[PDB]
Image (cartoon, rainbow, N blue to C red; front, side, top):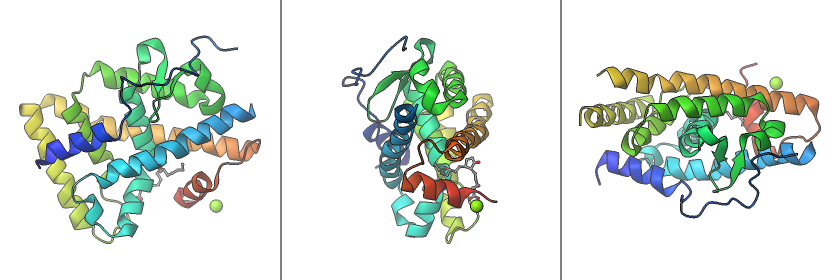
Length: 224
Ligand SMILES: *C1=CC(=O)[C@H](C/C=C\CCCC(=O)O)[C@H]1/C=C/[C@@H](O)CCCCC
Ligand SMILES: [Mg+2]
């Protein structure tokens, strides 16, 4: 019932099994509407799985529904990228998605554009730090459990955030490495802007219009 245990449990229960991965579409050197649609499908498919991870963070389910939505929606792309980066094999150009589908980076270029290159690069940096499951489960939680403008119960979010911070602190001790760990969180904000830049392009291009939920989330989150 420990907090770090519950966070690890949240992480483990919402990630695909390495023992049952889907290589049926994988192409190391591959030879467009359906690539863009794939990109959207990967985003939408990831949404329900991350929300399900969010709900397994202690205290998260206890917030007003408005606050849950605010936290989730604000951190979604940050979460998508982090979990992808941690799961994948950047040395081999392999991206492993939340449904267990394995695709080469080259297969992701048409849909994601320049963004998978940023993702794969980030995955390289993240993995070179050799962050254990416990520590990652903390960083993942902190990407979402953070103060946002428009929270009905910010002190509750603040309280939960610091509890996760101290979990990570205690686990690290089992000081230097902690700052570089928390330093991955502003780097995700940049990666999120980049996903947004990609959706922006695609929508402007208007070859495939984004599905309703992506569209709604994209439009609402723009501060202009
Ligand atoms: C990640 C980087 C961004 O550019 C946006 C930030 C936008 C507004 C600030 C929110 C913080 C607050 O509420 O105070 C975020 C991304 C948010 C996305 O996850 C929203 C979904 C995009 C549609 C797929
Ligand atoms: Mg507008």
